[PDB]
Structures are given as C-alpha cells and as structure tokens.
C-alpha cells in the first residue's frame, strides 16, 4: 500500500535526521530491523502452535476452525497467518531500499 | 448409556478423570503451606482462593509486596515436588518466575469451578467447543504446567466388558459431594450434545469395534505387527517420529472422527443387507455397495476421497525431513506413517495430543497409504506384466491380518476386514455407476490389478492358463506352450475386457475339449 | 487461473466439494478457493518473491 | 611478528576517533532504560505502529501455492491429459515464449 509506506518512511527519516547524537547510520537500520521483528512476533498465538514456526516449514496451517468463520474474517486470518512468519523479511527490503 | 455411543462416553470419562486429578492436586496443595514456610500465608490462602462471593487478584488484593517472593517460591517448590524422579521437566519448572506461576494458580482455580477453561486467546477463533476439559484443549490454551503434572503423576460381552469396565475405573476410591456433582452433570451434557450425530452404533458395529480393539491390544492383529514397526527405527531418529506423529494428530483431528463415523455407516449397511463361499467376496456383490457410494439417505460421501485427503496431509507432513519434493521415495520412508498408525489405533503415548482411539480410520487410511505409495503408477509390455505380478503379490501379501503360525479358519472379524479391504480396492478404480470391467476411461492397469486381487493371488492370465491345460486335450494340429498362452493373453489385451475374454475362452475351450 | 481450474476438477476434490456446506470441510479446499478469489480481485498489484 | 601473513591481511580493523554520544545499547540489558529499540519506540508519534502494520497486505498463502508447485506430484491427473509439470517451469517457459 504505497501511501502509508511513504508516511512511515518519512516519519523514520525525520526521527533519524533529528537524533544524530545517537543512531550512527548503521545502528538505525539494525534498530528498525529489530522493531520490525517485534511487530512480527506480536502476531503469534498458541493456537497454530509454536513448533509450527519456521522448522523447515511444512507444519504450517491457518486454524482449526478456519472454515465456518465468515467470508470476510477468513481473509484477515490469511493475512495474520502469513504476517506471523513473513513480515520482517518483506518489509525490511522495501524500507531499506 | 456408555455402550451405544462409544465415542461420547469415551469423551466424557476423559474429562471426568482430568477434573478429578486436578482437584486432587489443588486439595493437596493447601496443607503443604502449613508445613514449610511456617508463616508465609498459612491459612488465608484458602480465604483468598475463596472466589465464592470474587473475580481474582493477588496483587491489588493482598497489597503487601513482601508476599510474592515467598508465596510463589513455596508454590514452585510444591510443583517441582510433584514432578520428581524425571530430572528433565524439573528444569523447566524451576525457570517459571511468576507471573507464569500466578497465571497457572489462577487458571487452575477457574477450571475447578464452572468447569470451563478460562480462555483469553483470540476470541473469534473459538466456537463454544474449545472450553471442555481434554488433553487437546489444554495444549491449545497455553496450560502447559498442568500437562507436566498430569504426565509425571498418574501415567505409565467379553471384549466389551474388558475394555469398557476393567480400565474405565478412574472413579474408584472416589466419593461425590453436595457440590461437585453439578460439574459432572455439566461434563455429561457437554459430551452428549450430538443427539443424532455420531449415528448408527449398536451390536451391529459395536461388536466389531470392540473385537478389532481387543485383537490389537492382545495379539497385535494389524496390517503390520508393531514389533516390526519398532525394530526399524535406528536410535537417533526417534525424536522426529514423535514430532511427525504429534502434529498429524493435533491438526487433522476432526476429519479423523468424520472418517470414523462414515466407515461405521458402511459397516452397518453391509451387515444390514444380510455364508462366505464367494458371496460377500465375489465381484458383483461388492460392486453393489461400491454403487451404493455413487447413487442411509444414499448420499454417503465417498470414503476413498476422505482417506486420500488424509494421505495427502500425511505425505506433506512426512517431507519435513528433507528439502526436496521426495517424489517417488515416499516409500522407503513409510516408517513415519506406520508409527502414526500405531499411535492412532493403539494406546496413544506422548500425552500432548492424546484423544480418541480411531479404530476404523487406521485400517482404511493405512490401506490407502500403502496403495498410493507402493502399488500405483498413475503419477510417475512383458516386463510391465512382471511388474503387475510383483505389485499384485505385494498387495495381496500386505492385506493378510494374521500370519505367524495359527490355522487359517477365517473367524468373523477376519471376514469383515477382508470385505473392507476389497471394498477399498474396488473404490480405488471405480469411476461411475458401472462395473469396472465394462467401462472405458479406466486404466489398463487398474482392471488387471482389480482382477488380480479379487482372485486372491495369481493373475487373470495364469488362472485361465492352468484351467485350459487342465484339459490338456488341446494339442492339435496345432500349438500349446507358454507361446499359445501369451498369444491368448495378447488376444485379451487387444480385443476387449474383462469377463468377455474369461467366459468366451472358457466356453470356446470347453467345446474344444469336447471336440477332441 | 487455468492451473487452479485444473486443480479443482479431480476425483477426490469433486466428490468432496459436492457437499460444500451440508457437512464438514477439509479446511484446505476453502483456502484454495479464497486464494484464487483474492488473486482474481487484486490481479494487477501482487508480487511473488 | 605475524602481521604480514595471509590470515592477518584479509581482515578489517575499524579504528575511528571516539565520538561523544549518548550511551544506548542494542546488545542486552537491563535495570536501566538504555535500549535503542525502546528509545526508537519512544521517539515515535502516537499512531505509527498501526500505520506500520497497515502496509503489506498478504493475498496468496504459501500452502495454497505449494500444492501446485511443491508436492505437485500428489495430484491425480484429471481424466485425459498426463502429468502437467509444476507451476514454476510452466511460468518460466511461458514467459520466455
């Protein structure tokens, strides 16, 4: 969604330009990467269990009652199931370029 | 009841046992504080755990911060006292550091009152079912120390009597109360909410269920004996088998019960439509049922498609041991599926996925897995015939229950399993309401393999070869020798199939024998 | 969409999709249906990494 | 005496004059609020985490695209045609052609 991404990148550029008594230009990228990893790990639940994480992924599923949910909540479920594993990897690329 | 609806009572007594054991733990815990930590919280512990008349809070209520570092210390000491002599879980118990102990001590108090589970996860992925007590709804609500406790402590009409009574006696040396009976009533009304679902189950199929279960847990009557399963796992591969099993039984748990009830339905219909000479083991009779699957309400979703879907899930799980598609080497790696089958029909060890016992589903799914990983070519001519013979003898040698030394007199259970096997093989090839000998769009391979199975052994060609050289008579102006035999077999493979060739050669050489 | 349509016309998929909602679902066919619908909607923006 | 060998030459050394910057650390912890990720979260505006999450909408699940490219061999070929090689070879060939 290339209208919220622009706002986020502008905000981060401002935060970096105003604080150069920290953020030595390679600490900013690492800090942003770890912040993205925390934004990602705030998605994982006990349903859709732990080892169903990376583990040479073939254990991954959506939910035990994915069906019967709705026609519109079971796409939010797809988004959450994907973002729980592939959020930092695909957001950091765009951000850093 | 507990006799007609096997599975609903099997679901009720698990919950009863869980409630009883956790209540025992929580009633043994209070007297412990009156022995160590002489005046931490000795008596008012119960007065705070009253919850009679309420929500819960040990921080705001009891606003004396010099209480946690002793209360939770004593509680952790108690919990590590319960999980003794294992020397592995104790490590993870000592590393808890409340409030991962406070949450346990609150959830365990909430369970023993209202009989619920105190779910605080995403409250849109739960539907009035993920709240009853069971070993799976406890590995999905993050209640994990409870499972440590239940793992360390309390853990290791002939057949009907044996299984039902002689081991569903958790309730022995127990006494109800004025309270505590309402929670049992709640468990019961939770279990029996399917007042028509989980349909037909009575002495028709109930007897067969109990016979197969007793036979497995006494003699080892399965498609492969468990000793062979265990004796092929080299030492350093055992901790991944456990993980490929545990994940198959956690996620695909409702489809297994669905397949179970659907197999029970067809066993009911088989016994209700009615001798073993060739009726019940001939082609046309079994074809009648195989037609019953195309067109109890006569809908009956095909029980081969369900087993194929579960095979697909299992074959995707198995591929976690490498990073290549594993196309034709799904065999040479069937030890995983067979360990899962043992854990599914047998006594399920590894208490994190323990559930029902899935007798029928194991037979059907193991047959389907073997067929689809060994005896199939749809997804990959004399040597082709050698391959047909080799695969047919592998199949016919797999499907025999009892092997070792006992006399083969074909008791009733063996008859029923033979009928189920032949139905599962005639559903693999059938493609419509028309016998699979006269239909096109059925592979050359499948007609021949079905014929090779229904005759129990040899072939469709060598059978007629022996039958014709019986009337050795034919050796005219003329020719015999396997040469004439393969001549008649290519005549078969070209002209048309299948019983046309059988009967027409039969009678042509009957008249040939009466000729000379 | 051609590859998806080729997937959906199999024996074990047709015989199960017949009973779409009169019974339980494998929870896996619904995922494929949802994926193809969502793709056919936003077919000009997606990227595959 | 061993400074001019091959194992001492292909390495970097990174010396710079010491700057005088506020001490925030990305490495561990604790008991003292000196953490770069926490500081960055504190330097942000009110609504920015939810703006960070509302990018990157996921549409095609991995399990929906594997069943056609990886584990394609577990598919009954429909009545008629033989095996159709997976959805990666088809894609690259159709692209080139």
Image: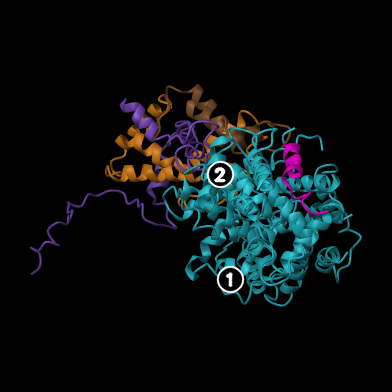
Chain colours: A orange, B cyan, C brown, D purple
Image coordinates for residue D43, horizontal then vertical, percent: 40, 39
Residue assigned mark 1: B90
Horizontal side, residue B458 vs residue B48: left or right: left
Query: Callout 1: few (<14), some (14-19), or many (20+) C-alpha neighbours within 10 Å?
Result: some
Image coordinates for residue B344, horizontal then vertical, percent: 66, 58
Horizontal side, residue B467 vs residue D77: left or right: right
Mark 1: secondary structure: helix
Query: What residue is at 84 percent from the left and 44 percent from the top?
Result: B273
- The answer to whether residue B249 is visible is no
Report the chain holding disc 2. B
> Which region of the structure is painted magenta?
B275-293
The label on residue B488 is 2
Asked whether the beta carbons under mark 1 and mark 2 sit within 8 Å of each other, the answer is: no
Marks 1, 2 in one chain? yes
- The answer to whether residue B173 is visible is yes
Report the chain holding disc 1. B
């Amino acid at each position: 969604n290339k209208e919220i991404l622009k706002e986020v990148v502008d905000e981060l550029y401002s935060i970096y330009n105003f604080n150069t008594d920290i953020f030595t230009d390679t600490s900013f990228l690492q800090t942003v990467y770890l912040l993205f990893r925390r934004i990602e790990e705030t998605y994982r639940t006990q349903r859709r269990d732990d080892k169903i994480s990376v583990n040479n992924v073939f254990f991954m599923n959506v939910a035990n009652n994915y069906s019967k949910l709705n026609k519109e909540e079971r796409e939010i479920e797809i988004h959450n199931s994907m973002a729980s594993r592939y959020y930092a990897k695909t957001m950091f690329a765009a951000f850093q370029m | 009841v507990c006799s007609a609806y096997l599975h609903l009572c099997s679901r009720y007594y698990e919950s009863v046992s869980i409630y009883i054991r956790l209540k025992k733990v929580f009633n043994g815990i209070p007297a412990f504080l009156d022995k160590n930590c002489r005046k931490v919280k000795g008596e008012e512990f119960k007065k705070l755990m009253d919850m009679e008349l309420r929500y819960i809070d040990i921080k705001k209520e009891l606003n004396d911060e010099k209480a946690y570092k002793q209360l939770m210390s004593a509680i952790r000491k108690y919990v590590t006292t319960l999980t003794k002599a294992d020397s592995d879980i104790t490590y993870f118990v000592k590393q808890l550091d409340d409030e991962e102990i406070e949450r346990f001590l609150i959830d365990l108090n909430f369970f023993l009152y209202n009989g619920f589970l105190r779910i605080t996860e995403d409250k849109h992925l739960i539907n009035a079912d993920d709240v009853s007590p069971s070993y799976i709804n406890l590995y999905r609500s993050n209640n994990i120390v409870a499972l440590y406790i239940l793992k360390t402590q309390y853990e290791e009409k002939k057949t009907t009597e044996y299984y039902l009574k002689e081991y569903e006696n958790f309730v022995e040396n127990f006494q109800p109360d004025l309270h505590d009976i309402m929670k049992l009533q709640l468990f019961f009304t939770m279990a029996f909410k399917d007042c028509n679902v989980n349909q037909n189950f009575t002495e028709t199929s109930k007897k067969l269920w109990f016979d197969l279960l007793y036979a497995y847990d006494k003699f080892g009557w399965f498609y492969i004996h468990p000793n062979e399963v265990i004796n092929s796992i080299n030492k350093t591969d055992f901790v991944r088998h456990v993980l490929v099993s545990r994940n198959f039984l956690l996620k695909n748990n409702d489809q297994l019960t669905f397949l179970e009830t659907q197999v029970a339905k067809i066993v009911e219909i088989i016994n209700l439509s009615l001798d073993k000479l060739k009726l019940l083991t001939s082609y046309e009779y079994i074809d009648s049922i195989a037609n019953n699957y195309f067109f109890l309400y006569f809908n009956l979703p095909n029980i081969y498609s369900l087993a194929y879907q579960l095979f697909n899930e299992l074959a995707i799980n198995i591929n976690v041991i490498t990073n290549v598609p594993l196309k034709k080497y799904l065999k040479y790696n069937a030890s995983y599926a067979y360990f899962t089958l043992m854990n599914m029909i047998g006594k399920n060890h590894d208490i994190y996925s323990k559930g029902s016992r899935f007798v029928y589903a194991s037979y059907i799914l193991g047959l389907v897995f073997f067929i689809e990983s060994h005896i199939d070519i749809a997804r990959l001519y004399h040597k082709d015939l050698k391959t047909l013979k080799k695969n047919c003898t592998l199949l016919t040698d797999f499907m025999k229950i009892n092997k070792n030394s006992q006399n083969y007199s074909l008791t009733h259970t063996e008859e029923m399993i033979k009928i189920l096997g032949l139905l599962t093989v005639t559903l693999w090839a059938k493609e419509g309401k028309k016998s699979v000998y006269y239909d096109d769009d059925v592979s050359l391979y499948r007609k021949l393999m079905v014929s090779c199975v229904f005759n129990g052994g040899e072939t469709i060609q060598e059978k007629l070869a022996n039958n014709i050289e019986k009337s050795c008579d034919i050796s005219q102006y003329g020719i015999k020798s396997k040469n004439l035999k393969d001549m008649i077999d290519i005549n078969l493979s070209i002209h048309k199939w299948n019983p046309a060739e059988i009967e027409k050669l039969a009678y042509s050489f009957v008249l040939s024998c009466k000729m000379q | 969409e051609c590859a998806y349509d080729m997937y959906f016309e199999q024996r074990h998929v047709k015989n199960l999709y017949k009973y779409h909602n009169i019974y339980n679902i494998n929870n896996k066919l619904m995922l494929m249906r949802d994926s193809i619908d969502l793709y056919k909607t936003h077919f000009d923006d997606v990227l595959f990494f | 005496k061993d400074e001019d060998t091959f194992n001492k030459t292909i390495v970097t050394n990174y010396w710079y004059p010491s700057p005088i910057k506020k001490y925030y650390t990305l490495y561990v912890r604790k008991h003292i609020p000196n953490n770069l990720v926490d500081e960055l979260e504190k330097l942000m505006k009110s609504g920015t985490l939810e703006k960070m999450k509302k990018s990157l909408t996921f549409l095609v699940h991995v399990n929906s695209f594997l069943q056609l490219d990886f584990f394609h061999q577990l598919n009954e070929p429909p009545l008629g045609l033989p095996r159709s090689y997976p959805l990666s070879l088809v894609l690259e060939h159709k692209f080139k052609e």
